[PDB]
Amino acid sequence: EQIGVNYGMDGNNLPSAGDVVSLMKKNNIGKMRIFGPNADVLRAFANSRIEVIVGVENKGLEAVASSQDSANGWVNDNIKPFYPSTNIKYIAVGNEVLEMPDNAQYVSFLVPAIKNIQTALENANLQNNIKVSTAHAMTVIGTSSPPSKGTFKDAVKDSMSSILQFLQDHGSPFMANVYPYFSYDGDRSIKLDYALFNPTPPVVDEGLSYTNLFDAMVDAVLSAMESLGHPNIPIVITESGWPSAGKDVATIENAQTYNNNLIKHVLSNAGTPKRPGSSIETYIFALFNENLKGPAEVEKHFGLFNPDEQPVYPVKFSLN
Image (cartoon, rainbow, N blue to C red; front, side, top):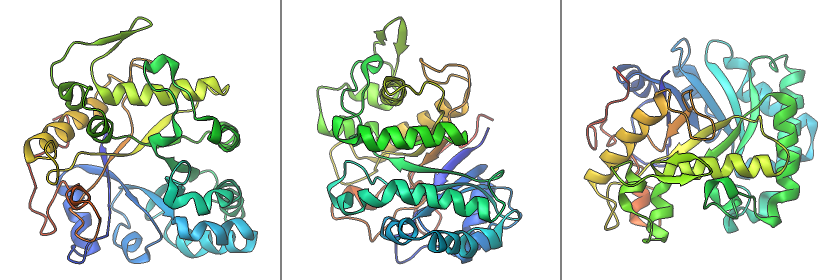
């Protein structure tokens, strides 16, 4: 029912955690994601009722993969002290680990880290309350057009099969970072209107109507999961957004259009064409412009808000 955001912290000038809680409450933002442990933040969110995804940082995967004691320590230090007052719902063990050159060094730690974090939750008696997954980039997807033909790249199938079985066994969601922006930027034969949810001819695929690129990308992931024998794993969109400066189509107007339209889309009952009828759990990337991101200028312009909490552009955060 309420939208989520990524609470990215890679800026040198961002608000206190308490101010961030107030900003989310004021704007009916009901879910948030952090990329790593942060006690000050989890403390600030106590009794806020905001649902929280806490990450294991990619650089922390090796420790928790290599030892159950380490994974137990991670849960006991970073999660257990804050639950249930802070409503932690998921641990996202790693971010964009697979099919990403910068993270190739961490790939061998991914699956054992997921499993050890799960065991650590069980050891803490938190397994009924908090589930475990990992956030994937779209680089894990091989074929994506048409969405019905979606597959995983051959190179990730082994890892992905293991991950999907884990998810099925634990009733845990696939977490996807999904950016029509990047798909469009890299292939200008895509219609910009389709990327933005603007009026555009729908794409009919096996009787299903794709009115926008977001739905097409998400459904390619669903088809890919089905192709590995997993038709019943839900998807949480851990990131989606559109930068407001730094490229021809990275503008105030386009970011405003994309994020307003995305919110209206995912909070509605539309669903996606393969899974219609229910809201899509989504975390906008990101709450603030983050002035230490880079190197490309677009990276510093993913915020719904400037660091002073002034909107970068107006956003309707609810269906009301």
